[PDB]
Image (cartoon, coloured by chain):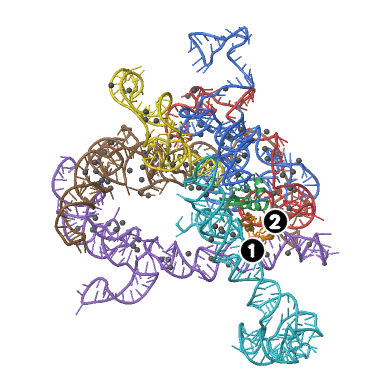
Chain colours: A green, B orange, C blue, D red, E brown, F yellow, G purple, H cyan
Amino acid sequence: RRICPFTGKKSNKANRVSHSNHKTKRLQFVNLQYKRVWWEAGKRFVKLRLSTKALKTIEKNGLDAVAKKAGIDLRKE
Amino acid sequence: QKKVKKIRKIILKEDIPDLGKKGQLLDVRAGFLRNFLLPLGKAEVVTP
RNA sequence: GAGUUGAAAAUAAGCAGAGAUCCGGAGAUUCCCGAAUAGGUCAACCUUUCGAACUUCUGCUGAAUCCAUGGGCAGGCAAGAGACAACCUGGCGAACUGAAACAUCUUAGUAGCCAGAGGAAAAGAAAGCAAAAGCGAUUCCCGUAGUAGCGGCGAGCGAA
RNA sequence: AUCCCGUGUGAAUCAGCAAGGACCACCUUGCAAGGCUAAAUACUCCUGGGUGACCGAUAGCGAAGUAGUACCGUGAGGGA
RNA sequence: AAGCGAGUCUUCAUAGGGCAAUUGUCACUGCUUAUGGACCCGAACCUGGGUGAUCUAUCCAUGACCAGGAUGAAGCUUGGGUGAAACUAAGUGGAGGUCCGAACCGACUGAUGUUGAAGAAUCAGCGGAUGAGUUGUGGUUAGGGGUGAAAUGCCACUCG
RNA sequence: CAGGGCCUAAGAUCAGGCCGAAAGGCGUAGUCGAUGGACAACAGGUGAAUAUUCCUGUACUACCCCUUGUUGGUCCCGAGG
RNA sequence: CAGUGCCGGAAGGUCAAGGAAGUUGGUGACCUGAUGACAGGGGAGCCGGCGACCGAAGCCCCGGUGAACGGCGGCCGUAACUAUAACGGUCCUAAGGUAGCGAAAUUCCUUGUCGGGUAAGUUCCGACCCGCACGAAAGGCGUAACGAUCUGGGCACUGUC
RNA sequence: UUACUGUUCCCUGGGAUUGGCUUUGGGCUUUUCCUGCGCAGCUUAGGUGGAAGGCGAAGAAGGCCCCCUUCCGGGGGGGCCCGAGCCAUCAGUGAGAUACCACUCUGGAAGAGCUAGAAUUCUAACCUUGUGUCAGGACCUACGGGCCAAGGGACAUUCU
Ligand SMILES: [Mg+2]
Ligand SMILES: [Mg+2]
Ligand SMILES: [Mg+2]
Ligand SMILES: [Mg+2]
Ligand SMILES: [Mg+2]
Ligand SMILES: [Mg+2]
Ligand SMILES: [Mg+2]
Ligand SMILES: [Mg+2]
Ligand SMILES: [Mg+2]
Ligand SMILES: [Mg+2]
Ligand SMILES: [Mg+2]
Ligand SMILES: [Mg+2]
Ligand SMILES: [Mg+2]
Ligand SMILES: [Mg+2]
Ligand SMILES: [Mg+2]
Ligand SMILES: [Mg+2]
Ligand SMILES: [Mg+2]
Ligand SMILES: [Mg+2]
Ligand SMILES: [Mg+2]
Ligand SMILES: [Mg+2]
Ligand SMILES: [Mg+2]
Ligand SMILES: [Mg+2]
Ligand SMILES: [Mg+2]
Ligand SMILES: [Mg+2]
Ligand SMILES: [Mg+2]
Ligand SMILES: [Mg+2]
Ligand SMILES: [Mg+2]
Ligand SMILES: [Mg+2]
Ligand SMILES: [Mg+2]
Ligand SMILES: [Mg+2]
Ligand SMILES: [Mg+2]
Ligand SMILES: [Mg+2]
Ligand SMILES: [Mg+2]
Ligand SMILES: [Mg+2]
Ligand SMILES: [Mg+2]
Ligand SMILES: [Mg+2]
Ligand SMILES: [Mg+2]
Ligand SMILES: [Mg+2]
Ligand SMILES: [Mg+2]
Ligand SMILES: [Mg+2]
Ligand SMILES: [Mg+2]
Ligand SMILES: [Mg+2]
Ligand SMILES: [Mg+2]
Ligand SMILES: [Mg+2]
Ligand SMILES: [Mg+2]
Ligand SMILES: [Mg+2]
Ligand SMILES: [Mg+2]
Ligand SMILES: [Mg+2]
Ligand SMILES: [Mg+2]
Ligand SMILES: [Mg+2]
Ligand SMILES: [Mg+2]
Ligand SMILES: [Mg+2]
Ligand SMILES: [Mg+2]
Ligand SMILES: [Mg+2]
Ligand SMILES: [Mg+2]
Ligand SMILES: [Mg+2]
Ligand SMILES: [Mg+2]
Ligand SMILES: [Mg+2]
Ligand SMILES: [Mg+2]
Ligand SMILES: [Mg+2]
Ligand SMILES: [Mg+2]
Ligand SMILES: [Mg+2]
Ligand SMILES: [Mg+2]
Ligand SMILES: [Mg+2]
Ligand SMILES: [Mg+2]
Ligand SMILES: [Mg+2]
Ligand SMILES: [Mg+2]
Ligand SMILES: [Mg+2]
Ligand SMILES: [Mg+2]
Ligand SMILES: [Mg+2]
Ligand SMILES: [Mg+2]
Ligand SMILES: [Mg+2]
Ligand SMILES: [Mg+2]
Ligand SMILES: [Mg+2]
Ligand SMILES: [Mg+2]
Ligand SMILES: [Mg+2]
Ligand SMILES: [Mg+2]
Ligand SMILES: [Mg+2]
Ligand SMILES: [Mg+2]
Ligand SMILES: [Mg+2]
Ligand SMILES: [Mg+2]
Ligand SMILES: [Mg+2]
Ligand SMILES: [Mg+2]
Ligand SMILES: [Mg+2]
Ligand SMILES: [Mg+2]
Ligand SMILES: [Mg+2]
Ligand SMILES: [Mg+2]
Ligand SMILES: [Mg+2]
Ligand SMILES: [Mg+2]
Ligand SMILES: [Mg+2]
Ligand SMILES: [Mg+2]
Ligand SMILES: [Mg+2]
Ligand SMILES: [Mg+2]
Ligand SMILES: [Mg+2]
Ligand SMILES: [Mg+2]
Ligand SMILES: [Mg+2]
Ligand SMILES: [Mg+2]
Ligand SMILES: [Mg+2]
Ligand SMILES: [Mg+2]
Ligand SMILES: [Mg+2]
Ligand SMILES: [Mg+2]
Ligand SMILES: [Mg+2]
Ligand SMILES: [Mg+2]
């Protein structure tokens, strides 16, 4: 799904609005990337789809904090 | 908005070209740090 | 407490005051299909080495790869799965219609679909109201009030 | 304004932070970024009682008898 | 509107003018108004979710079928041509979206039929009939679609 | 004899896998799926209603049973068909 | 090759989000004014408006391209007799219909005119050209074979009469 | 359809994913140097201040020449030669000495700095391949998994 595992981001439901005020259904999507991330405690990369915000947060708190809050085992990844 | 150069402050654990001697203090772009230095054990991101 | 073997007579045999038929509580059995679940199928069948498939659980075992992951084997009355009128919560989400046309607006976050759970659900213990005086989580009804307002300031919508 | 989300940036800890319908000063009120909680309220496939200025076989349930049957439709469905 | 208040707004001016100087209410019954299907019955349609390729439109797999007769391409071999080759009867050979014609597929004209024998037929004739053929069984594509040797045709007697 | 206890085609479902508001979509091994491959039976008789099915004759497949002969066979895999 | 499309070009103009020098406003610790029930200036901070300059494609601009969309005219005057016009003048366009065909599935007037076929022909065949309004891949003009095609005539044949 | 309002395919810029080295270069600078024809005149009067002291042998006036700017009036300035002077209220002039010194303006230069833009590389993100190679009871020339390699490469893709 278009969902980040780590922050739980969802695509957001939004109206495209013209200059004429005429509304239209539209989807804003999470910015998802297929990234490998280094895991120091596993001595190895992990392939993930991530939001970019998640990538940020992984820089800030370290990967393990994030994956523990989101409840996803780096081993099964 | 405006692009803001990301600055990670680091310590070098080995000598690398253009950077310097082992045990050295620097400031870097985030991409350079996490995609090159950090997987190879070469640098260490420092927040004491 | 007297007759009984469904509707439902007739026939044939029984069972019955050591208490039948009958009524209530708790158990037992419950072929085949159906979540269907040993494998297959054209539901109610077939083939089988006779097996609750798969996912969680307990143990043994241990790839690429050291720790691991995956896989393999075994235990176990074994947690789930499916069904469910309306109500409810979430997700997607119209159009005719109204505006005496129509596009913003209305219809309406209605119907419908999908997923989920309960006897109710949701909400809920002030980063809240208020106004110089005070209140003391949420929900529901009366009222404020068709008021303040919103609005191609049109149709209408409408608080606290 | 308050509230909640996509993209990007990105704080402060009580000498703070937020709210008081742009915004600033002052004062009042409050403590976001962890959870859970009964009742009052909504409903009828139903169960047990009760009532009816409700129907009485063209009515009342589609259905007082094989009724979701017969029959029709490839089917969803229709339907006495 | 601050605000004033039997007055007040407009005013330099009460000078004049405007508006005010008072009034029951709660029910029931009726008539009307408004909001909901709103006096009843009657569209073509619009959107949402499903159901259909047993008909027909394309294709896919795997099978089957096309009496009988004609005509006689290339090629080939023979024999006259020159040193090579050309050119020409001959025989052989059996090509063809060839010919005539049953099955089979169609549907050109006419007559009948028109509360039909039949919601498209019968009768007499007619076209194709080894191919761009016919057909069986089992499949495929689904409605903001599909399929179309293209008619807006066909998608279960329904299709702008 | 015809299907099933055999094998696969078109196609279908599809463990894990990739994607997707949900339902689901794609897809690998696997497994389904005959209209095809494989595989052994005929004549006469009876006969209210069945017959390559029941009767009488000769057959034929697949197993099992014994004798004899060998010691490794079985599947997975390599091939021809 | 003007219009339209398409392709190529890069000098100039135009050109959004976004940046951004810089100004500008509200508030305000404060500083003064003032016979009215107050007022005027104002640091830091916070908040708001404006904003020169930078800012791509596209468009305007320049060039090609008709088996791309399409388009292919008027007015005069002139020759041994009437006549007609090879030839000239002018007008206007991007350019002004060439080859071939032509009363045609195209022709209005129109049953055009002529010839043929018929005793008699609004149809048919051939030709004229005065093409209302042919014309070159929306192809032009030919053409053997073919057609349950459309259309004219003839022999045979018949209750079609 | 060159009606209106939009949506989508698609193209192009910011942001994000996203990095290293090097160049070239548009606009701002950090020391510091170049540069000014109101007229009265020792004469191409820089404004404002400290202002009787400065510039010299770490070697000037004066002539021999190299360069650059140019209103060819003259200005900065390198080499050499030269050897004891160019000087102040000295009077003009709104503003003073080329005796000197500080923030600076007209435009130029240079090494140093911010931001683009642009072009070039590099490899580790990211993309693309592989009958290359491992791998479980056994396979995966069955998709895929790990490793390795190969080609691209901060483009592209994806999001806003
Ligand atoms: Mg950044
Ligand atoms: Mg029971
Ligand atoms: Mg039984
Ligand atoms: Mg089963
Ligand atoms: Mg099943
Ligand atoms: Mg172990
Ligand atoms: Mg190990
Ligand atoms: Mg394990
Ligand atoms: Mg198990
Ligand atoms: Mg359930
Ligand atoms: Mg369910
Ligand atoms: Mg329940
Ligand atoms: Mg509407
Ligand atoms: Mg409408
Ligand atoms: Mg209307
Ligand atoms: Mg109307
Ligand atoms: Mg309750
Ligand atoms: Mg609750
Ligand atoms: Mg409390
Ligand atoms: Mg609390
Ligand atoms: Mg709040
Ligand atoms: Mg409020
Ligand atoms: Mg939201
Ligand atoms: Mg944020
Ligand atoms: Mg903090
Ligand atoms: Mg706020
Ligand atoms: Mg508060
Ligand atoms: Mg807190
Ligand atoms: Mg909050
Ligand atoms: Mg809390
Ligand atoms: Mg709760
Ligand atoms: Mg009756
Ligand atoms: Mg009835
Ligand atoms: Mg009666
Ligand atoms: Mg008066
Ligand atoms: Mg109606
Ligand atoms: Mg419509
Ligand atoms: Mg529909
Ligand atoms: Mg279907
Ligand atoms: Mg079918
Ligand atoms: Mg079919
Ligand atoms: Mg058929
Ligand atoms: Mg076929
Ligand atoms: Mg036959
Ligand atoms: Mg034949
Ligand atoms: Mg023959
Ligand atoms: Mg033929
Ligand atoms: Mg023929
Ligand atoms: Mg036909
Ligand atoms: Mg016939
Ligand atoms: Mg025939
Ligand atoms: Mg024939
Ligand atoms: Mg043939
Ligand atoms: Mg067809
Ligand atoms: Mg038509
Ligand atoms: Mg039907
Ligand atoms: Mg039909
Ligand atoms: Mg039709
Ligand atoms: Mg297949
Ligand atoms: Mg599927
Ligand atoms: Mg799966
Ligand atoms: Mg498969
Ligand atoms: Mg089978
Ligand atoms: Mg068969
Ligand atoms: Mg068999
Ligand atoms: Mg057999
Ligand atoms: Mg019989
Ligand atoms: Mg027999
Ligand atoms: Mg015999
Ligand atoms: Mg045998
Ligand atoms: Mg084999
Ligand atoms: Mg042109
Ligand atoms: Mg052009
Ligand atoms: Mg041109
Ligand atoms: Mg262009
Ligand atoms: Mg441009
Ligand atoms: Mg701007
Ligand atoms: Mg600024
Ligand atoms: Mg100000
Ligand atoms: Mg003041
Ligand atoms: Mg002020
Ligand atoms: Mg510009
Ligand atoms: Mg041409
Ligand atoms: Mg004529
Ligand atoms: Mg005519
Ligand atoms: Mg004539
Ligand atoms: Mg005639
Ligand atoms: Mg003619
Ligand atoms: Mg014409
Ligand atoms: Mg023309
Ligand atoms: Mg034409
Ligand atoms: Mg023609
Ligand atoms: Mg043409
Ligand atoms: Mg033609
Ligand atoms: Mg011809
Ligand atoms: Mg034909
Ligand atoms: Mg972009
Ligand atoms: Mg970037
Ligand atoms: Mg590489
Ligand atoms: Mg492989
Ligand atoms: Mg591999
Ligand atoms: Mg390279
Ligand atoms: Mg990029």
Circle 2: element type: loop
Q: Position of residue B32 (x, y in %)?
A: 62, 58
> Can the viewer see residue A22 in this picture?
no
- How many C-alpha atoms fall within 10 Å of the one at disc 1: few (<14), some, or many (≥20)? few
Is D43 placed above or below H53 here?
above
Camera-nearest residue between F22 and A45: A45
User: Residue drawn at (57%, 52%), measured in percent from left and top?
Assistant: A16
Looking at the rendering, which quadrant does residue E136 occupy?
Answer: top left
Q: Chain of mark 2?
A: B
* Residue at which label 2 appears: B46
Q: Chain of mark 1?
A: B
In this view, G75 is above or below H63: above
Quote the CA–CA distance across marks 1 and 2: 20 Å
Task: Say which amino acid is labelled 1.
Answer: Asp
Compare marks 1 and 2 and give the one earlier in the sequence. 1
Q: Is residue E5 left or right of residue D10?
A: right
The amino acid type found where label 2 is placed reads Val
Residue sitting nearer the eye, G36 or A64: A64
Q: Is mark 1 within 8 Å of ligand 102?
A: no
Residue B11 can be seen in this image: yes
Circle 1 SS class: loop
Q: Position of residue H160 (x, y in %)?
A: 59, 54
Q: Mark on residue A51?
A: none
The residue mark sitting in front, 1 or 2, is: 1
- Tell whether label 2 touches label 1 (CB within 8 Å): no
Q: Position of residue H31 (x, y in %)?
A: 71, 74
- Residue at numbered disc 1: B18
| Residue G16, image quadrant | bottom right
